[PDB]
Image (tube, coloured by chain):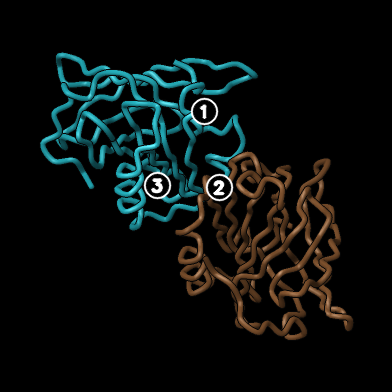
Chain colours: A brown, B cyan
């Protein structure tokens, strides 16, 4: 599968947009109120080497916002979390300035909890990001695959 | 694409929707999507038309619908009037394993395309998914679903 090499998390700060998603289980994304249907809107590296993830979510008929705290681990691209019934966030690839590929999993049931996303800096559908997303995903047993158009990227959440 | 010299007399029998894909996300998301239909049976008519018996999760139950696909000059293109669609285009089939088709609305085809990969047995045929993902490479799909055997059996009869 994929992975990031010598990842500097300080060069990841700024606004992000969720361009595409994919999950191993269909029920993890199918709908707008899905448990994993979260829209990464901002990443914030901490001085201590951790990551704060700001994501928007369709709850109760409105667009709520939530913050997940990703604590660092021994591996530079692996983080540990405790939110959305997930416990590990793996960064798959990033060029810091355009795209970022990452995944979420639960170490108990990784086949029923794996869900990957493709983040982009601008609210455009970057085709190069979709290349590396589909290239990293062709080895994963994804049963639902989403991709957003600019109109959906321009503020679904 | 466009199943040339399609012998509609050899498509009858029980079918299962193994995978789906739509140009818009809202066309296949959630259980009650307008294009979240589960094809069960195909029945060719003596005059060369097609009867499509499919299942749809409506109002908390598994309702059955019958769409009558009238033939056209093109052997693999049929005319319908259901689900806000007016065309059915069979892309490829070997009659005994897989069948690929697509529904659309001739008014706005970019907002109504939805393709499916049907199989004879409720098993995950990998070759069928291979040709499905390859025949969809020219279509602007934004949501792609794929079902497991457990879902393939209990998608009604």
Q: What residue is rendered at 41% in x and 31% in y?
A: B17
Q: Secondary structure at mark 1?
A: helix
Give the alpha-carbon distance from disc 2 to disc 3, as whole Å.
14 Å
Q: Which residue is mark 2?
A: B25
Q: Residue furthest left?
A: B5
Q: Earlier in the sequence, mark 1 or mark 2?
A: 2
Residues at discs 1 and 2 both on one chain: yes
Q: What residue is rendered at 49% in x and 43% in y?
A: B145
Identify the chain of the residue marked 1, using the numbered disc in the image: B
Residues at discs 3 and 1 both on one chain: yes
Q: Earlier in the sequence, mark 2 or mark 3?
A: 2
Which label number is shown at residue B109?
Answer: 3
Q: What residue is rendered at 17% in x and 23% in y?
A: B10
Mark in front: 1 vs 2: 1
The number of numbered badges drawn on the structure is 3
Question: Is B99 or A32 nearer to us in this picture?
Answer: B99
């Amino acid at each position: 599968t994929q992975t990031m090499k010598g990842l500097d998390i300080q060069k990841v700060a700024g606004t992000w947009y969720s361009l595409a998603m994919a999950a191993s289980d269909i029920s993890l994304l199918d709908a707008q109120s899905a448990p994993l249907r979260v829209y990464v809107e901002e990443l914030k590296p901490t001085p201590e080497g951790n990551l704060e993830i700001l994501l928007a979510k369709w709850e109760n008929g409105e667009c709520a916002q939530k913050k997940i705290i990703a604590e660092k681990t021994k591996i530079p691209a692996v983080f540990k979390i405790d939110a959305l019934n997930e416990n590990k966030v793996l960064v798959l690839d990033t060029d810091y300035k355009k795209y970022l590929l990452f995944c979420m999993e639960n170490s108990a049931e990784p086949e029923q909890s794996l869900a990957c996303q493709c983040l982009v800096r601008t609210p455009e559908v970057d085709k190069e990001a979709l290349e590396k997303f589909d290239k990293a995903l062709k080895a994963l047993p994804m049963h639902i695959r989403l991709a957003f158009n600019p109109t959906q990227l321009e503020g679904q959440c």
